[PDB]
Length: 144
Length: 143
Image 1: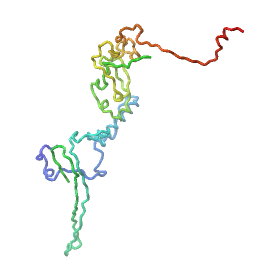
Image 2: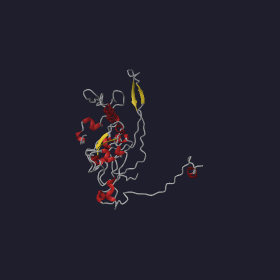
Image 3: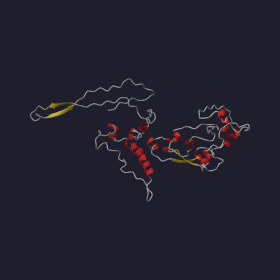
Image 4: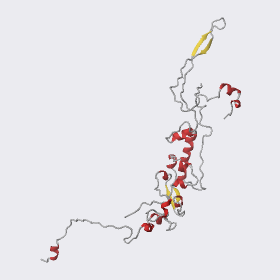
């Protein structure tokens, strides 16, 4: 929530924010506040089995939310409904491309560099956005 | 058995009456609707002059399974309409059974005159019955 580009720090402002590593077991853990146990109160000597039933149901709603419905839009999708991008002010994703960056090695050829190599990665790529209709004034930003 | 659907200018949607609208009431989240226990509410929660002493146990989010009839409060005191111009059970006391059972007086108001009670009818009942029955001639004749 920085208010001005001037509230950003050296690195961020010049290179952009940092993003998440590709997903793996250690970089895609369940949200840190994930419940590991759900307590349910009980009268000194008895337990309301009907309440216990509700308790679970309630928990279920809580979990679903924590695990994958943390964003309003996703909760509404949960019900089988939908939301315009104006509903939560989300930028509209118009096109997403992804590709691997490969290249070649350069062979060292002098007395000491003979048998050495330097990797030069150089990948060509196309990123094409199909004719899009702009309903209101604004910006079309493309990032990498 | 002649009856009038219980329309009333005093009944309102359950949700219109709730003071604190909760997720459980509004959301209509299935997960909840199928595993909660019944809900105890009172006629006060359904009619403006509803009797709070009459408690009923309804099924969760039932108000989302059916809509109630509506009568502008204006008809509330015009004599001649067979509406329940008073929350059911208003004059029988905090007693459920007495509210559920139809109180015919509730309608006295809308009739010019019950010279023939509230309703009345006339019909022809054509009945044919096959049966073992000696003819009247046989009954009255000895030999």
